[PDB]
Amino acid sequence: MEIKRFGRIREVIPLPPLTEIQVESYRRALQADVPPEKRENVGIQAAFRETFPIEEEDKGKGGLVLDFLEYRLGEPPFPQDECREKDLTYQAPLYARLQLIHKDTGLIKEDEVFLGHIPLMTEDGSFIINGADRVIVSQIHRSPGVYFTPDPARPGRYIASIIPLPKRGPWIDLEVEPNGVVSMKVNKRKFPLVLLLRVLGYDQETLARELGAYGELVQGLMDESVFAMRPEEALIRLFTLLRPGDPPKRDKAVAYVYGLIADPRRYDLGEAGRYKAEEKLGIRLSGRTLARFEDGEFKDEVFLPTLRYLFALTAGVPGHEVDDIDHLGNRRIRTVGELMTDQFRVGLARLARGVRERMLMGSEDSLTPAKLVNSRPLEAAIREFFSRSQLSQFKDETNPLSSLRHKRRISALGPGGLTRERAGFDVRDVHRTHYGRICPVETPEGANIGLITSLAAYARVDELGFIRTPYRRVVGGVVTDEVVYMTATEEDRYTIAQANTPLEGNRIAAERVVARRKGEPVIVSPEEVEFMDVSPKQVFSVNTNLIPFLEHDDANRALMGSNMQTQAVPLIRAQAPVVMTGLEERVVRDSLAALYAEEDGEVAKVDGNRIVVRYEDGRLVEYPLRRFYRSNQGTALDQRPRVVVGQRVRKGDLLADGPASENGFLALGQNVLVAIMPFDGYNFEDAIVISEELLKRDFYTSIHIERYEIEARDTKLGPERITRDIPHLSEAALRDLDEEGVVRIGAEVKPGDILVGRTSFKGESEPTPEERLLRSIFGEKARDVKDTSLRVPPGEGGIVVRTVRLRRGDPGVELKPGVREVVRVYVAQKRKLQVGDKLANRHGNKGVVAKILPVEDMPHLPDGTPVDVILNPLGVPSRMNLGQILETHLGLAGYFLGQRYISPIFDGAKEPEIKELLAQAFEVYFGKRKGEGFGVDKREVEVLRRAEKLGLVTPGKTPEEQLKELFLQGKVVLYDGRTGEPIEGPIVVGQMFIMKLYHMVEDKMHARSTGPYSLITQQPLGGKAQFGGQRFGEMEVWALEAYGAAHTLQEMLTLKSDDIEGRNAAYEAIIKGEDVPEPSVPESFRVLVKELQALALDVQTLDEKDNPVDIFEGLASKR
C-alpha cells in the first residue's frame, strides 16, 4: 500500500511533547533529580523555605531558629507493578536536613526525619495512588494582580480591585462617592485613601500636585485636612478604624502584614506579580509585594500607582485602561507541580504549627528530632490530595489516546477559590484569546460545558501558567520561520494574520489579505501584517486534530466526534483510517501505546512475551510486553510484536504495536465499505444496519476484563471460611471450583456460577427453633454455616485468566482491619459486535446497530462485493458535517486504488484532487470489467436512464463515459440483493472509518423483579446482584396523571415501591395467580404522619362523617 498527502503549507515546526504540561510541572514542582545547588527553587524547595525559618521569640523563653539546609528524597519503597498487584501507593521517601538553634550555647542538628511519602509520576505523566492509575487535571482562575472594573448598579464610574491570593490576605477596592466619602476596603468596612498615603509619608501637597494636577480628583484627597496634619499618628488612627478594641500601641506590627511577608505574596520576585504591574500600571516594586521592615517607616510603590491609574483611567487617554478579565493574560493555568506544592506547603504549615508547641514542651536542649517533628500532618495532607482531591481522578484509559487527553485537560472547578459552580456563561464561552491556547471544540457536551477543557496543539505553559500561543514574526512583507510564544495581553498590540495567506516563502502574495487585530476580523495589507499564525493545528486540541476534514463539519457535531474517540475501545483487530489527518502517528508515539526502539541494532528474540533487541553498541535489552493487562475501564492492553527475528532496527521504530495500533498508527475501530442510503426502518432516526459479514470476520470484536473480589471477614459469630464447601446442594456447581475454594483458571463462568466459595454463620446470635426441627428430620448434623459465596453477577462473565489470594502471613501488603484475607478473580470475555452496540465515525455520526443483515440480501455492488454498513442519509443534512461524505468519497478511491491517504486539517485534500483519484479508481473498477469479458447491465443502463432524467449524467454520452461521470460524483449503481434489481438512482459508497463505543455499566440492561429495600426509606434498592428499581419521577407521574391511569399510578406508589404490606401480598398474590391485592397504606405516608407527630402537630385521618379511620393498622392503639 502507498501514501499520498495533499495539502501544502510548510509545517515549520514539529508538535511539542504532548504531556509536557504534566511532566514538566512535576519536574519544577519537585526539583529532586538535581542537587540543592541547582537554582530552580520553586515548588517543594520554595514551600519549604517559605515555612521553615520558624521564629518563636517571647512568651516565657524562646529565640527559636529551626533552619532548612537541603531537601533530599531518593529511594522508592516499592516498585510500580508491585504497587498495582498489591494495593500500594507509589511514593518517594523525603527527609530534608534540619538544625534547630538555641539562645544558650548549642545547636543540635538532627539530620533526617522522614515525614511525608509523596507520590511520583510515571514516565507517561500519570500516577499510581491506590491500585488505579490517577491523573491531576489542571485548573483556571483570576491571576493575582490588580484590575479596574465598571461599578455595579450606578452607570457612573468604575472601581479598582487589588487581588492577593492565598485566601488569607486582604482584597482591596477603590471607589469614590463624592458627596463626602471615598471607599477603600480590605476585609469590608471602608476608610480614606489618603489616611494611608499619609501613614506611608505622602503629604497632601506633594501628593495632590504631582499625582493629580492633571487630575482634579485630587481635591477629594486633601479634603479631611484635620487628620492629614499628623503623620505617624495616622498609623495609630487607622489601627483605631479597624475594629476589636485593640491597644493603640503596636509600633509596626499590623503594617508589616500588609507589608512584606505573608498576605502579599512570595510568588517569584520579578515576574510573578511585577509583570501585571509595569505594563498594566505603575512602574516599580521594591520587595516582591508592597514590602519593607528596615526602618519602621514603610515604602509603598504600589498604593499610589493604583490611584494614579484610577485618576488616569477616569480622565482620558494615558492609554485606554479597560481590562477585559477573560483576556488570557489575566487567566493563569495551574500545572501539576503547583497543585502539589500547595498541598505540600499547607502541610508544612500544619507541621510548623505543632512544632511551635513543642519548642515550649521539650525540657532542655535535646529537642531536635522528635521534639520538633511529627510526620502525621504532612502524611494526611499530601495523601488526602492524591486520593481525595476533586481534581485528581481515575486515569481514563479506555484506549491510550483517551488517557493522554485526561492527562492534559484543564478544569475550572476546584480549590474553590478560583471558579465554583455559580458563575458560568461568561467563562463558558470561547473567549477571543482562546486561540491556539484552548480548543473551541474539545469541551464536554453537558451542564459542565466550556469549564472543563483540554488544551491545544502547540499550546504551552511558559514560566507562569499563561497559555501562550505561537505566532511567527513577519517583518514587512516578509514572513519568518521564527516564532514568539506570546501572552494573551501582548497578542492584542499587534496585527496578526492567518496561515491560509498565499505564501511564496517569505513573501505574502495578496494585497488584500485577512488579519485580526484584537478579536476583530480585519482585512489588512501585506505591509501591516506584523505577525502570522503558526498552524491550522495549533488552533485545536490533539483529540480534535485527528478529524479528517474538520473544515467541512459543523463545530457543533465535531465535538461529538472528538469526545467519541475518547470512548473508542481497542479491537483485537486494529486498523488505521483510510484517510487520516496527520497526527495518528504522533498520538500513539507521544501516548505510550507502542514500544519504540531506543537506538539502532538487530533483533535477538521475538517472543509473544518479549523482544530482546541487540543494539549496535554491543548491548542487548529485553523488552517485556504487557501481554494482557486490565485497563481501569476494562479494555485490553496488549503489545503485539511487529518485528521478525534478526532485524536491523532504525532508532525509534515500532517493535510492538500498542493496544489499538495497526502499524505505529492510531487505530480504533475499522475501515469498512459503506453504502449511504435508507433501508427499511433499520436506519431511521439514528440507527445503523450492519452486514453479518462483519461478524464472520472477527472485525468488530473487543476483549473485556472485570475484576470480581471477595473477602473473608471476621465475624464474632465465627470466621468466614473460604473453602470448596458449599453447604446445601450440588457438586455440579463445584466443578470449576477445582482448587479448594478458588475457581480454576480458564474456566468458562456463566451468570450464576460460584467464582469463589465462603462460609459465614447463620443467625445474628441465636440458632433457629423451626430450622432446628428440619435439619434433625433429614440430617440433624448439618453444617450451620451460610453460603456467602462470590457468584457471577447477572450480565456476563468469560473465562478466568488470573486469580490472587492474600492469606495470613502478608508479604508486604496492606490488609484492612477485620479483613482476614482477600481473593481477586480476573475474568476476560470476547465481545463480538451486536445489535445493542453503538458505533460512530470521527465526525459525529453516532448511532446504534439495529439489524445485522445476512450478506445474502444486503446492497451489493455490480461485482459481487457487498456493503458492510448502510448509513441513513437523513442524519447528514440537519447535522452539518459533510466531512463524512467527503471521507467516504476519498475512501471509494482508496478501495480500488488500494491506498490510504493523509488529508490535513484545513490544508488537506481538495474536491478536484479527489475527483482525480476517483478517475483512477474507475479504471481499476471498470477497466478490469472490460478485460474480464463483460460490459453493461440492463440494470446498469436502467439506472442511467433515471440518472440523466435526474441530472447527474450528461445526456447523450456513452454508458461507459456516463458511469465515469457518475463515479467521479462518488456514487455508483447498486443492486438490491434481496431482489437483484437495481436501486433506482446512483448511491454513494466507500471506505469510512468507524469505531465502536465502550459499553458503560448502565448498558448492562437492568431488569428487576423483586429485591432489596432501603432501611429508613422503604423504596427498592439494588447494588451487587439485584438490579435495583427504576425511578418514577414527577414528570412521569403526571404522564400517568394525564392518562386515566388511576390504578397504574396507585400501583407505582403502593404495590411497587412503598406499600410494605402491599408488595408482600402482591407477590404472593401473583404467585398463586390471584389478582394483586388492593394497596394498603404506603410507608411514605406513615413515615410522614409520625415525622409530623415528632413535632407537636397531630395528623389524624377522618371518615365519611368527621370521625377517625386507621392508617397504622393496629400498632398505634396502646399496650
Image (cartoon, helix red, strand yellow):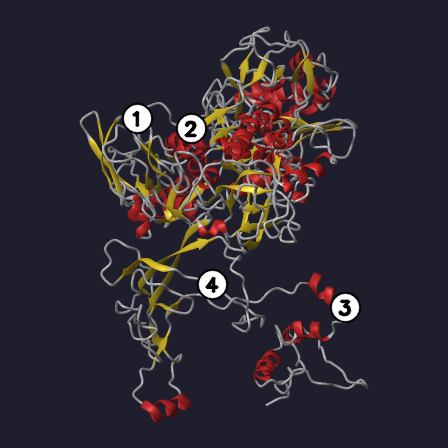
Task: Give how far apart the Cα atoms at labels 2 and 1 are.
Answer: 21 Å
Q: CA distance from mark 4 to mark 1?
A: 47 Å
Q: Residues within 10 Å of mark 1 (few under 14, many from 20)?
A: some
Give whichever of discs 2 and 1 has the lower sequence position.
Answer: 2
**Where is the C terminus found, in terms of image quarters?**
bottom right
Q: Earlier in the sequence, mark 3 or mark 2?
A: 2
Residue 650 disc label: 1
Report the disc number at residue 17: 2
Q: If you read the primary sequence from the N terminus, does the residue marked by circle 4 or circle 1 appear first?
A: 1
Label 1 amino acid?
Arg
Q: Nearer the viewer, mark 2 or mark 1?
A: 1
- Disc 3 vs disc 4: which is toward the camera? 4
Please name the residue that numbered disc 3 is placed on. Answer: 1043
Residue 795, which numbered label?
Answer: 4
- Separation of marks 2 and 4 at Cα, in angstroms: 42 Å
Q: Report x, y in % for residue 1043.
A: 76, 68
